[PDB]
Length: 461
Ligand SMILES: O=C(CSc1ncc(C(=O)O)c(=O)[nH]1)c1ccccc1
Ligand SMILES: [Cl-]
Ligand SMILES: [Mn+2]
Ligand SMILES: [Mn+2]
Ligand SMILES: [Zn+2]
Image (cartoon, rainbow, N blue to C red; front, side, top):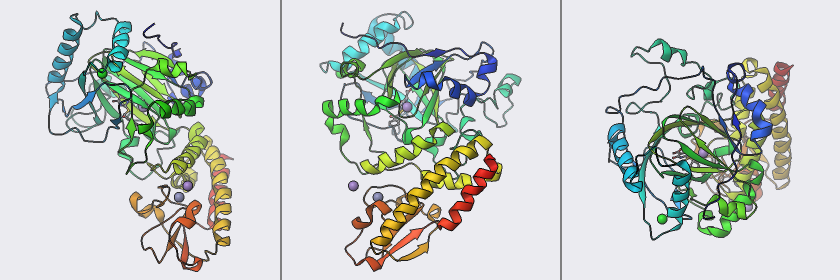
């Protein structure tokens, strides 16, 4: 009555045969799971990766978190935190003491139902000022992946068994059914797994993944992680609810790192007709989030999770829509979607054939859109043009000054404003000079582009 738990998300228990190929499995469950936004996956009894560490030698910099509903929090940035330092042992000791002191009970006898109830009480009661700490970063020499990775150091035969698993999250990016694989541009924050060390009540605010990608989260060990998820189709519903209750979160900001997010009771969303689902993720289980599926949660206690973004062929059209949406909001991109597409086209001979077919369809849309934009800017009197290798420019040197989109297919420059670019939607936002002073900078002619797409079609057969 104070808190009503959302209904449970789907839980899948695949056979080893069903489980072995993550991409085939995800495609199979997608008609069910995309209706709930998140789902949980229990691997077959078979699958049991080694979880081995000396907690005395693993160090990380803790982040501090206040727990107030609707209060703005800043998105985690790589290597922030500060200079302070915990080992996994001293953090665990701190975390277990916090929880057992908080409830005056041993940590495992606190029911998950109760921690959940207490979480939503304490975040709404700002007479309470509970602060907690957590770890969040990519693998480093001081704190590595919880999955086996190659290095020597001699690996056990059981560790070797899991090196090339499709569910070893170090691998998921670089597998052939993943389209982020082919991206040459390092984007560490996105293609590499994140490591999360949690404690009771430490939480992750409501968000969707960059570029509306999937995510997959594995809980290596510890107390459960509680999740709330919202299906992709209700993303704008949720955002509307949020913009009315917490308008502060929707101000334009300097960059991608200054992104603001918040804790919000799922009952509040359910009250405004946003469908929400929940789950408790236990050690050894996976949670999968689908494209544009909002999710949030908190930890039941001391634990260690690993998560990574990924993008399947199914995602490609949504990826294009996402960048369009980013343009409308003037939100920064993590990478150029078109650059990714053209990179794959340039590698058509070595592409998985299903990938080739789907890339070809997205490329066809890209080319027709580009054709139309170029005709529009020509009618605005932009006549001069020159080829430009956009992929060579640092990202922050090829952003539209208006909408911040990362340019690749083309942009407009002007001698009156050296170094500045606009995308072709924002030709009028660059300078006040006469039209003929403008230059179309383009990566490819239409005559370059159609053969590239043809190579994909041949590969797809
Ligand atoms: O703030 C975040 C990090 S997402 C995150 N997920 C899970 C945990 C966790 O299980 O402990 C966490 O600490 N953080 C974010 C990410 C993308 C866009 C905007 C914000
Ligand atoms: Cl509070
Ligand atoms: Mn996430
Ligand atoms: Mn505009
Ligand atoms: Zn623009």
